[PDB]
Each structure stands twice: as structure tokens, then as C-alpha cells.
Image 1 (cartoon, chains in turn brown, purple, blue, red):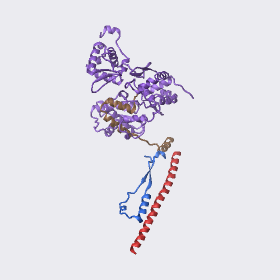
Image 2 (spheres, rainbow over the protein chains, first blue to last red):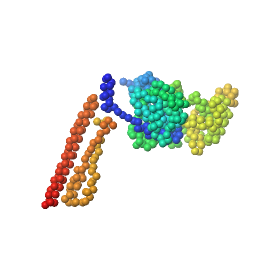
Image 3 (cartoon, each protein chain N blue to C red):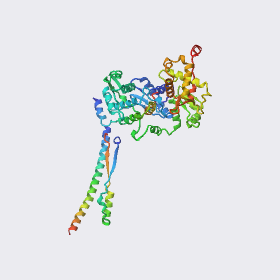
Image 4 (tube, helix red, strand yellow):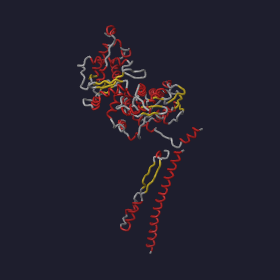
Length: 50
Length: 384
Length: 49
Length: 49
């Protein structure tokens, strides 16, 4: 119940969103004519896991 | 309070590096370990690399952004652009799902097909599209972006009507790194680095070189007058001193290359050489190129130049010398196939580049660090 | 209110065409005064998106 | 709740100032409008005479 009242408090301010972003990057992946170039673009997007 | 860089700090830093991020819910010990030194680590990361450490309730993450992206860096399980496109579409999908929301595999496939922004439509009746989606879903689940209720996606390979029920986990929110504006004001990915450079004017050279060195197995000299290599030459000694104080690595320097070696790798760590046979054949090729320095006279830049024809002759020569002991996979494969795979492999670890047009092979000085041969009992008793 | 990204924007009048039929002297001051004073400021607010 | 009350108080201050501003804008335009109408009526009387 306290969580719900708190949520009512959160419902006045919280909202965010970032979906739009993914479209341009997916398209850029579309232009990837070769998957090593695409790997490089991926490393742009998030770097290296290791 | 005070803290010092010790075994724990090295291990936490290394553990952080060899994974994209560490989750509290599954790796609480490493997360806590990282947390005790987090103060020194944040300062230090800023000082040497300039990377931003994000510490959260559910995760800790380092946007290991490279100085110049390279093919091997990317998620390797993926093999085509379509895989990345499906990944991005999946991300877009997760933006549409509330935390702990439950969704069907079919809804995800349909939504990805509908949203897919390319000119050429994605079709699920095909096998390749389904394979791309399955690879995307496995990678997604690896980062716990999606939880598993029930079903089996592997059956999806030969049965598109297959169904599975997944649940969107909290991590979907935080997956995307921190990117300041509307990406559209940017016109090409190369423009992204200019962001990474608005924050690092202070000792930009040291942080740039450090990032280049620490990420890649090695750092190749661009030319005779490379400012970066001169810089490396300048601190020279203190870089080595710092590395001894701060990490497992041991620095090496040569006229046309510089790189970090590692003395004690561990299970979770990645290193070269490793089990894959192609490394073995690469080392044998290294010895063969080393053995005729004058015929394979290295250019001023430390590179050794051979044409695709010469490489195929060399591969035949290698099958002649070391071939009885190669793995049956390569022993049974034609020369050109072996050539394609070995050259891609050598590219991934940055030993060499193949010019696409002129077919010239550039073997980087880093290649000459290691050479390999069989045990003497085979040298007698083998491909002798 | 910073989360709302307040913002203002000036409102202007499209200089009405009948202004062209020059009236000079006695009317020039009134046209100039109206041209200066006709501009007013507006406010629009990004309230919860 | 404290954030909402703070933001509401700021919005109240802003809206009161903005409403005074708009009252002034409308009042000024009305005063000039009255001057125009007065002069037009006077002009019509003059025209008739």
C-alpha cells in the first residue's frame, strides 16, 4: 500500500523514454554492407565486452 | 578514509573489462568487491582512460569506448548486419514493455517485422531471418535483458509457428549507454568520437594512448612520425613503472610497435595464443616469415609484405612442413579456404591487414613477437 | 520547474498589406507606434511531455 | 509531495505574473483600439459635416 501511494507520488514526475534512438542506429546497421564494418559499428555503439 | 590499489582493485578492474557489465543479482561478490574500491577506481579511470563509471542498484558498467573501433570488439556471436538490426529492433521492443511485463515470442517477431525500418523487408518464413532472430534472442538473454518463463526458441529453427513466453527484466532500461543529444543531429557514426573528445582535452594524448594500448592486444606505429608513438617513447619508462604498479601486464616496446603482455591469465580472461588451431598455424606462419626476413623483407614500418598468391604458396609450404599434425579440419580443407579463414582470424587479433583491392598482405610487427614449432619427437617422427 | 523545460516565443503581426497605401505625415507616427507595440511575448510549457 | 508543492508554488507565481502581463497586453491593445475607434467616429462626424 505504501508502495502504491509512493507510486502515485512517482506518477507525477518519473516518465522518460529513449525508443526513438534505436531507429537511426538500426538503419545505420542496414547500411552495413559487410559484417566486419558492422562489427566496427557495433564497437562504436557499445565498445568491447572484453 | 583511505584506500590503495591492490590485488582487489586489479581483479575488480579486470573482471569489469572482460564482461560488458556485472549484475548485482547474479555476481554479488564481484559487485561488492568493486564497490569497496569504487572511489579510487572512479578517479583512476578518469585519470588514465577518461571513462565514466556508472554504479547502479542492479548493475555496474564501464562504457569501454575504443579510440578507433575494430571488428573484433563487437559482439562476436553475431555474424551479419541483419543480426544487429534485429538486436536494435529488440531493444526498441523492450522500450515498449513495462518492467516484469510478460510477452510472447510471436508478439516480438511481429513487432520487429512491422517496425523494421529498412527498405528491404524482413520475412520470418525464411530460415536465415529466423536464425538471426534466434541468435539475437540468445545474446539478449545473456545480458538478462529478457528472462525465461517457458518454451524453446531453438525449435524455432525448423518451426516458425513455435512459441515461447519471455519476461522483460529491469536491465532493458539501462542497456543503452549515455548519449547526450538527439542522435539525428549527427549524420554519421564517425561524429560520435567528437563527443568522446569534448570531455577529454586534459591530457588527451595520455588517455587516448592508454585506451588504444589497454583495449587492443597491441598498438601499431602509424608512420615514421606518429605523434602517439613519439609520446609513448617520451614517458617510456614511467608508463612501464605505472603498469607494473597498476596491473598484470608487462609493457613491451619496439621500433614499429608497442603492446602489453600478460603474465598470468585466468579462466575468465581472454588471451592469445589459445586453443583454436588457427593460432597454432599463425605461429608456424610467423616462424616461416621470420625465417626468411630478406625475402619477406619488412618495410620501414615493421610490416612484412606478401601477395595473396605468395600467401597461398606459403600455406602450401606450411602444409608441407607442419601439416601431418594440423587438425583434420584444416588438413581436409582446400588452400584457399584455409587462406580466407586464417586471414580473417589474423585480422581479428590485429596481426595483419589484407588490402582489398591490390591483395597486398601487410603483416604487422606485432606478428613477429611469437613463433611456434612442433615437439622434437614429431619434428623427427612427423611432417619431417 | 526545470524538468518541464519552460519556453517563450514572440508573437508578431504579418504587417497588414493595407499599410502600403502610404498616408504619410499625420498617420506615419501611428503606423510606427503600432509596429513597435504590436509585438508580444508568449509562453508554452513542456508539461509531462 | 514537497517537490510537487514547490513546483505548484512556482507555477502559481509564474501564472500570476503572466496573467498580469496578459492583462496589460490586452488593456494596452484595448486602449489603442479605443483611440482608433474614437478617432474613426470623430472622423465620421467630420466626414458627415
